[PDB]
Amino acid sequence: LNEAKDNVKYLTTLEKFIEPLYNGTPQQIIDTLPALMNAIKMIHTIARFYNTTDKMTGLFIKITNQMIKNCKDRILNMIWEQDPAELIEVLGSCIKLYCEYKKCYNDTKEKVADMPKGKTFDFSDAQIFGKFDTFVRRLQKLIEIFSNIQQFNALAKHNLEGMD
Amino acid sequence: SPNLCKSGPEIKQTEDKKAMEEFKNVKIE
């Protein structure tokens, strides 16, 4: 009761708000990401164990899995049926969201480099081989596929007098 | 005389053709 009440009382200072799972627009997913990565900066007063650096990396891969759940949810409503226009918009906005994730998670990794400076006693080796790597490669494939589709649409409209 | 007129595309589709030329400009860009 003592250690658990202790560890839990130190984890209390988490500012959770379920923005990502209730977002329906890439703008909402983005400004969600700043919100979560600004609430996360309270890494310090949290307890060593429940906030173990490896457990933090696990919560990171879980945040990315929730992020990719929401990404598939917003993509459901459909770039492979709809015309190049919604594809341009959604691809642009999803790339902006990915850059936002990358950079805000780089600031959070600055916090993860803050952690050892005072806690060099133990380290949690980089376990970056998660589903997020594979599916971010998948999203890169989608980006390139659909951007080249975009440019080819106009280029084919320039090439052959038989447009159709 | 065989090259006189085509009689369907030249007449009222010609303004559309000039719009299509402007489209070819947007294509040039």
Image: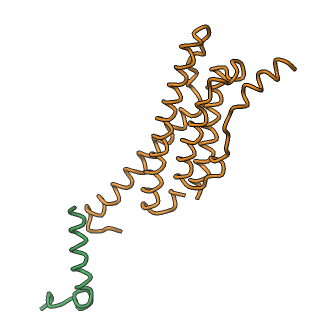
- The quarter of the picture where residue A121 lies is top right
Query: Residue farthest to the top?
Result: A121
Chain A's shade in the image? orange
The residue drawn where x is 87% and y is 20% is: A1
Residue drawn where x is 76% and y is 22% of the image = A7
* A124, B22: nearer the viewer: A124
Chain seen in green: B
Toward which corner of the image does residue A112 lie, by quadrant?
top right
Question: Which residue is more in the foreground, A116 or A152?
Answer: A116
Residue B2 position within the rendered picture, expressed as x and y whole percent measured from the top left = 15, 89
Residue at far left of view: B1
Against A47, is A26 above or below? below
Question: Quadrant of residue A11 in the image?
Answer: top right
Count the marks: how many?
A: 0
Q: In this view, does A108 lie to the left or right of A155?
A: right
Judge whether A49 appears above or below A88 on screen: above
